[PDB]
Length: 314
DNA sequence: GGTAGACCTGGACGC
DNA sequence: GCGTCCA
DNA sequence: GTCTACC
Ligand SMILES: [Ca+2]
Image (cartoon, rainbow, N blue to C red; front, side, top):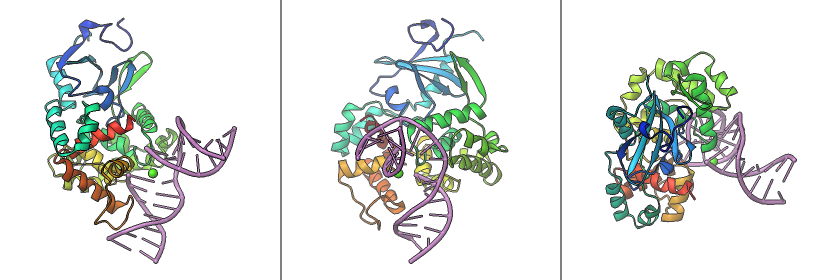
């Protein structure tokens, strides 16, 4: 009853709503599609994870987004706490308006879009996003998810326990920068990326000015921000773009990897023109990225997510 | 400047 | 069952 | 995917 992960049915008095149609958000389409790797559908249609340093379970109906929080006496979320949810899902950005525009300028996006509504971008914490994606290079979403999990249990603050699941907050810079962190990560199976995590944590804290240097990129320009990130070990154009798009408020950023290449070739018959190479390469990926921006506009990254997400789901 | 190859790891094929 | 793929 | 050795 008062134990385990909650469900809307089981503990009615403990949930609160947020007007939000599925047309504007589909948890099942955004939470497991490679934006964040920390949400789990513990119960059908119920997703649990850490959001703004507290554990939440989310679930939706046709017109509402139901929220519950586990912090004191168990109670429904407060308006302020809920706002944190609204901010996390950038619910101010209207998806109907964006889909309309992308659809207007892209007959293909229109077709695909009809079947995959509610795919939007989560507004993630810079740090969690930096290291989670440092873990994403040359690797699949399933492993990535596990790695990030083991990483948070070993170095993140212990939050609360639900059933046999103990939640952890994402590790701090100091923690990741710690002595012997890499060796520990290797044992947790992060592979050669173990070194990137340790190295980037130290680089940020000991060479770039700390947390402030990262949190300052939100005011910077996509171009600036992207160049800065690339300095860090294990962070290339692709990783940098994900961070730009998902944590640094650069909605025009478009991550180019195997998925978008297939899409570009199969659905747009795209080919590199200025670049030197015919296949994937630093020059061509950059070009593909430009192609998508000119096609979709300032929120290309968000559009990219729609097709990217609808691709995984097929 | 613009390539090739190696690289931790493990669920997927495919023979 | 194993070696090559591939994310 | 990122990084490094190399024409
Ligand atoms: Ca590959």
